[PDB]
Image (cartoon, rainbow over all chains, first blue to last red; front, side, top):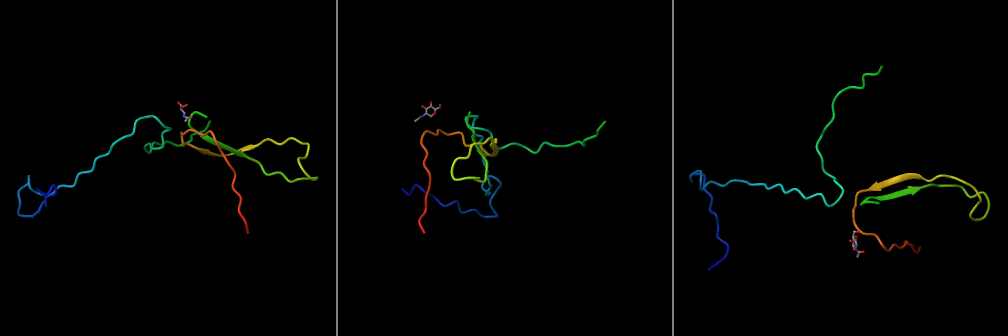
Length: 48
Length: 48
Ligand SMILES: *[C@@H]1O[C@H](CO)[C@@H](O)[C@H](O)[C@H]1NC(C)=O
């Protein structure tokens, strides 16, 4: 048998048979210097 | 050092012929978070 099989997605299909796009985000462990972070900045300077 | 490649540099004019006697600190140029082993190095030359 062929290992690959066509999905044959159709709009008339049900929710379970409908196509869905899935993205997996995997985070590397802390073995090297960190290069990815989040935007974290606010506030003014307010002197004196 | 601890997974960071640090490059300090300085450009000094040569008042004389070679290797003048003088003092001038080397300012830091570049810091890279590469975090891999370094044990051997070599320089590059080109021919015209
Ligand atoms: C690379 O560096 C790691 C961490 O210091 C060390 O355990 C390992 O033996 C090094 N490998 C080589 C080939 O020098």
